[PDB]
Length: 32
Image (cartoon, rainbow, N blue to C red; front, side, top):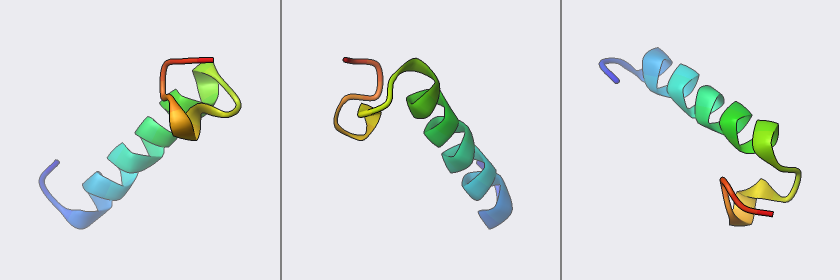
């Protein structure tokens, strides 16, 4: 990170990483 908008883009990329591998992912980011 380095500024707010970059942390929000990073959190969006983590959120996409979550939703890419799995649907229920909010309990297990790389897990079924």
